[PDB]
Each structure stands twice: as C-alpha cells, then as structure tokens.
Amino acid sequence: GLLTDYGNASASPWMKKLQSVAQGSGETFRILQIGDSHTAGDFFTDSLRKRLQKTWGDGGIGWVYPANVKGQRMAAVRHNGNWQSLTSRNNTGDFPLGGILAHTGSGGSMTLTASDGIASKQRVSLFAKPLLAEQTLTVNGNTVSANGGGWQVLDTGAALPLTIHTEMPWDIGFINIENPAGGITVSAMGINGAQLTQWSKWRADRMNDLAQTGADLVILSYGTNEAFNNNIDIADTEQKWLDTVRQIRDSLPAAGILIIGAPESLKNTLGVCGTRPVRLTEVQQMQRRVARQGQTMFWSWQNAMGGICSMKNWLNQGWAAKDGVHFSAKGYRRAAEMLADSLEELVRSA
C-alpha cells in the first residue's frame, strides 16, 4: 500500500545483498537518505536507523556531520571541537555531496563521541579537501595524508571516541564510521529548507562523491519546500528530477532508489482541516510519476499519515508541530516506523 515498487526489488542486486546481510554475511548495507528539514532533524532517519539495525544488524553510525550544524541534528554522535561548519542552505561554496563542509583551521581539533550504541574499533572514511596537496591530518594519532589536491575520500581505521587533528587547514565533508562486523547503516544527509534541484549548489563532481558513499539504498526525501514555491514549474522540475534519478543510477549502478512523497503540509492551520499549499498536490503527483518513469520505489508519506486532511489531526494530537509543516519527535518516529514496516515486508516477500 504505502510502498509502491515501480522497479523489481525482488530481482535487484541490492535486495540480494540485503538478504545476504540478513543471514550474517558480515557485509555492510548502506542506506543513505538525502533530503530537507525532516531529514536534517534526524528524528525520522534515527527511528529508521534503530528499527532496521535491530532487524538486520548494527553496522555502525554511518556518514555523519564533521561538526555541529546550526539548526540541524545528529542523533548517533556528539561533536566537541573548534571546526566551523558551512552549509548550502544560505551559502555558496565548493560543497561535496550533502551540502555541508567544515573549516578546520590550523591547530584544528574535533572529537566525535558515539551517543548510545557500541564504542570500540571502526572503519573510518572522510570527505576532505586539503589547502595543499600531500597535506596530512591525524585520526586518533595516526597520520593520514591526501593524494593530490581537491576533494577526495580519506580511508583509515580508528575507534570511537574519534579525534581528528589538523595542523594546517582542511575542509571536511561527511565522515563515515562503520563497524567491521557489518550490518546496516542509515546516513542522514539533510539540509533545512532544501529542494532536490538544489544539488546544483554543490560541486560539479558531486556524483563522484555519491559513487564513493557506497550507498546500497538511496532515499530521496523532498517535496515540502518545492510545494511552497507558488510559481514552481512542475514540468521543468519533473525533468530535473528524472535527470537526477538517472544520474544516481549511473553513479551507483547497484543501488536501489526510494522516493519519499511529501507529507501533507498546511499553508495555514485555521481550517479544522487546514488549507494546503497551492502547489502541494502537483508536487506529490510529480514525485510519483518520477518514481514510475525512473523505475524507483515510492513511499507515500501523505498516505502514511492517513491521506488528505490528516495534518491538522496530527497537529491536534501533538504528532506534528504547530506550524502544520514540521513534525514532533514522536511524529517523525511514528512515520519512520511505518516506512521500516513497509521495507521489512518488501524484503520478507523474499
């Protein structure tokens, strides 16, 4: 119902990897959710994280912020250091995939500490761009060096708590922190206010970054902010979305793709039903058509909530925030548990 497969998940390379993980192959199945504020809060993705890791294995915390990001949250890790984040929300820059970077400065320091969960040894990768080629940094004392200049991914091995020292300045992107025993990771790549087309704000080679995430399931979670643009061109947007899906399949041939249809939002809540933004329905329908033409999976967040005229009720019962757009912690948890439910069923239907 809530989940519609317009591809063939049962015969896909990524289902086969997941089934094999479910049986104890020791591999790591990486779920990567790229989206807007709903994603950036981590309440949704973290619920998804906890659910699917109990079911199929805790593969570690995955790709996390390199530093605290104002107005955004990482549930799985805590940050202590002097690095300074920058995001594509209000700014321009040479962003790697995700639209977040952090300026380390000289004499730079960052420690990441695991919230709950396990706390021993880990595989570590970092998106990173040095000021100078061949430049180095340390990860738990161990010297790690760039190869040439420009954004690249640095691979090494460490353990949590993770401490990173930069004698000279770097820009750092997301940091991958994987448990060697394998399992599931759920990575959240959110930007408050973001629309999918705004990957255009990130660097030209952003798809090479995507290719390097090792994502087995890319979840695209947008629509809310597109829906508040009263003058949005749906046909232009639809083409951009199909292009993006195409680029994702080129970049990650083996990954599945899930598009999350936008939740009901309200332009105002004075209705006892509220009133929807004028372009919301067109945006949601566009997203489903893209899913079908791109042969992706589609999960209807609006239908998860109960369909049209459901947001007002969610608000009244405290599962959605007062603004009729964002959700409460338990609202996001609830919604993601339904998504997790939907995915386990899809898998169970072997």
Image: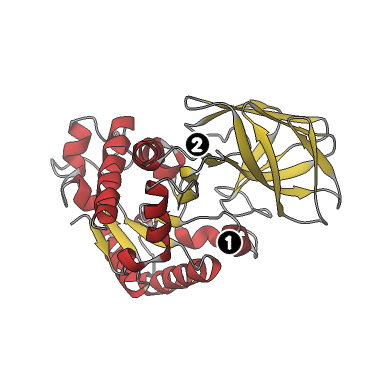
Look at the image and tell me whether residue 324 can be seen: no
Displayed quadrant of residue 46: top left
Display coloring: secondary structure
| Vertical side of 5 occupied by 264: above or below | above
Left or right: 307, with 158 as reference point: left
Residue at the (34%, 75%) spot, across then down: 293
**Amino acid type for the residue under numbered disc 2:** Gln
Tag count in the figure? 2
Describe residue 148's horizontal placement relative to residue 341 as left or right: right
Residue 348, x across and y down, in percent:
25, 52
Instruction: Tell whether label 1 touches label 2 (CB within 8 Å).
Output: no
Towards the viewer: 235 or 148: 148
Q: Is residue 139 left or right of residue 148?
A: left
Q: Nearer the viewer, mark 2 or mark 1?
A: 1
Q: Residue furthest left?
A: 272
Q: Position of residue 54 (x, y in %)?
A: 36, 36
Give the residue pinned by disc 1.
211
Residue pictured at 54% horizontal, 60% vertical: 199
Label 2: which secondary element: loop
Q: Which residue is mark 2?
A: 72
Residue in front for this viewpoint, 232 or 148? 148
What amino acid is found at the position of numbered circle 1 in the picture? Answer: Ala
Residue name at image x 41 percent, y 62 percent: 256
